[PDB]
Amino acid sequence: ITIPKNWLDFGWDIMTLDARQTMDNIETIINEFPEDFGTMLKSIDPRA
Amino acid sequence: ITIPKNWLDFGWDIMTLDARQTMDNIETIINEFPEDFGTMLKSIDPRA
Amino acid sequence: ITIPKNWLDFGWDIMTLDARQTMDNIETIINEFPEDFGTMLKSIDPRA
Image 1: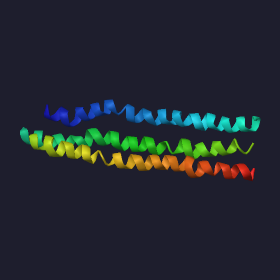
Image 2: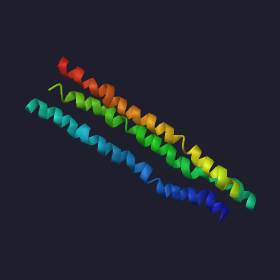
Image 3: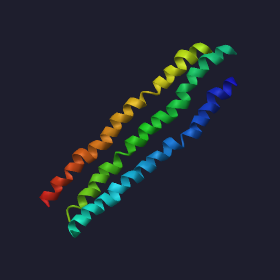
Image 4: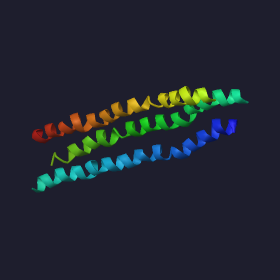
């Protein structure tokens, strides 16, 4: 109990860390809507 | 072994939690770049 | 065992509350890009 608590629970908060290493990418993908397409709205502005 | 159960438990709340809290700081920090370089792409477009 | 569970486990998620002050600030900085640099696209626009 005591030793796995200190290091494997840490390891399974690290199982949980997969969120807090992928939300970087997901938020970049959020930001890709204004970056890759919010740009393109400012291209629809030229078209208009 | 209860002395370990005392000190190691709130102790591991550095290990478990910091691996996540430092990384989300990093995820959000990195998400500045989809807005820094974001605004650079969003400037190249309206130049047209 | 119970004293950490009452004060220090709580306390070390409170050490984990440090990111839950930084995270706002960093996200405001993520926002300072589409705020300042994002309004300054509309400097690059009339300059164009």
